[PDB]
Length: 223
Length: 58
Ligand SMILES: [Ca+2]
Image (tube, rainbow over all chains, first blue to last red; front, side):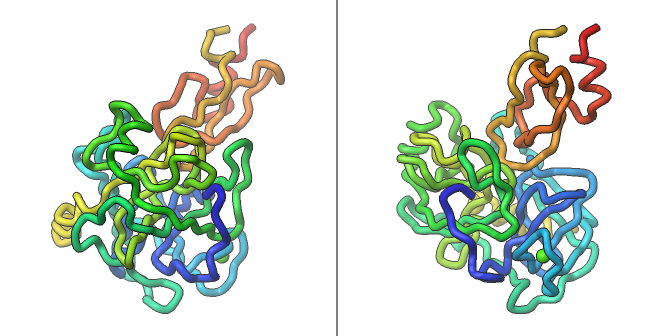
């Protein structure tokens, strides 16, 4: 997260870190056995770390659980990034508490202008690199589809939504993918892609979760 | 050596943090960089051995 702030400790209880040796992506806990992330975050072996604030220090609130099932959306395109969503079933149900909690799926699609919270342990710099120990937060609005389309000519599908600022300065970055975009208590977006980080005229592009509620529910029920 | 070996490491548009290797022509050896997870260019390898075999010249 570039241009954000350090989240209050455990104030984003649904945020998880996907780890395969090192932190490589984020995710959101939707029920005690399932996490939703980005399809490009796929790896054959994934360990989900919940209740994290400082990913480099054993604090005492963490829960480490391995992924038992990893299911990418059947229509995910690795080049266009359309349908960039993935579900992870945990090997065992996590213990829900104030620091490890679920986030609700969208009741319907949120309109442009809706203010949201984006979070993650990704790079905090637009130029160069700084991997933060502490979870970063960013308050940003869903942008009008026309502005998203203008920023990324011919690259935006109905399954994508731009969140951020046309003037740049604040954005999600490498290490944030798969993470949450929560608006009014609902997971409306998943960190997906963008050209650079926090660059003017190139706000981050996110998977539009409201288009996948049925797929998510059907997949969970069948697995 | 191949042309792609002389290009700077390409993170790409995706936002994951995937550690990959690239040939650093100035340094004369393969080093690590952060790959975003999609649309990789050719100077991107999953191992130092594969990187040096391909871009080592000689
Ligand atoms: Ca920790």
